[PDB]
Length: 565
Ligand SMILES: Cc1cc2nc3c(=O)[nH]c(=O)nc-3n(C[C@H](O)[C@H](O)[C@H](O)COP(=O)(O)OP(=O)(O)OC[C@H]3O[C@@H](n4cnc5c(N)ncnc54)[C@H](O)[C@@H]3O)c2cc1C
Image 1 (cartoon, rainbow, N blue to C red):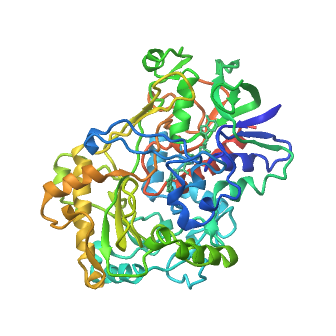
Image 2 (cartoon, protein in one colour):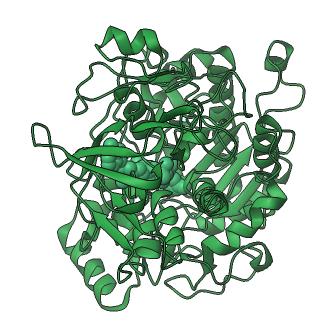
């Protein structure tokens, strides 16, 4: 049998599998619930990413419970269900977080190994900078010294330019008190307006399966099974005075017979922020009251399982623009799409290599904001963000289809420092039934107050000279008057959604602490022979879209595992 098993084949799970098998005497089995990523056009051409999920064979098809903060709406909660995990369906944007995120992870676990300086070594293992598809001069768009040159994931500057780029840059000069330029987020200082960097190499997706699992596939000590959903972690004995969890049961689908396999050393859960708590609950590790309400016997009582869920909420907003160079028609006119598909297929250049956004703004509330009279600042620290703004050359909205007429740019906000916390729980003890995902969006005065300010900021930005001949009007007339707080708040609660960055449902904490699910070396508290390496362990939302930090976790976690061999 195998030394390790390998719970999901995702953003962090593929790092662990590929790193452990560098040593030819260590065998790993990866169990992935989903299908192959191989020759899925929508997962290779960057521009086609938004279409892949939610309603599809590549998605788990999760939704949230009804949100009172969103006037009663449930929203889709997409997750990738295939080789590469969510790294095969994401928008490829790459950044690591602020220095304050990592120093706070160190301070709260007691382990200086997490921690901005000590983590930089993994950015170098993790990434290499390669040319943008259009091969433009990237001089002054990032700082080469703070990025990798030899690591596994290919990253680059935007591969196709847009009419927004020069206007964003001119706003950073016209409006520099509020919107100054940031040369590179890799400094650990996220604030300001920076050029996007994305996990794209040679005009296509660089994902965790392309970058780690595929090169490693010729190894005889690595084994990868797809269509293999783990349905139970099995309490396999008692070792080191604790219940041991080194066996798993897996099946192809509901109703099929289950296969049992064991690890000699450890089972590694890399099922992500939704997949990991629910699997623990299904195996009897979680809140005793919740488990017995659904007919499950508790083996380890730990109420932190599935709690402390943080996410970045999303606010979308489209504006009509005077332009024929937006990406909207690629999605409406088949001739145009096919001309750009041909160029992409033959040369890996043109519109299909384009990103969701070429520029990103990371922003704070004023130091004397009235909200601070009743909330302590929820930012990771004074050099970190309250919100983000993302500028796209088309219509972008997760819940409203692109209109048939009009050219658009969109201004999407993400709330980076929420006060809200939610949970993930079981509705039933059937591993094939969907979970109850309740992020509790806009359930605090800080969260709604900040999104109102975010909209006023968006409107000062679009009112600059650079936009005068370009922006015509908002798609939604509630975005016309920046002084009308009632109209703005109505807009936010009818439109806010998610930007897909859940963390925290299996939080790491100090050894012995009375909250958290894992120790700082990522071992499950109250159990022997089980380790968690994915997004679920991060105890706070970072200053980053979450592939960047999650790859660092995948990287320290592989080392943490080797250190106990
Ligand atoms: C539409 C969307 C857009 C996004 N946009 C971006 C972006 O631009 N940039 C960015 O940085 N982040 C983005 N994200 C964030 C990022 O993709 C995730 O935060 C991160 O990749 C997840 O890392 P992971 O290793 O925790 O989980 P995953 O990559 O989700 O992997 C978990 C794996 O576990 C498998 N699994 C789950 N349960 C089981 C089981 N019981 N048995 C077997 N297999 C199982 C899943 O099928 C999956 O393959 C996006 C995500 C989505 C859904």
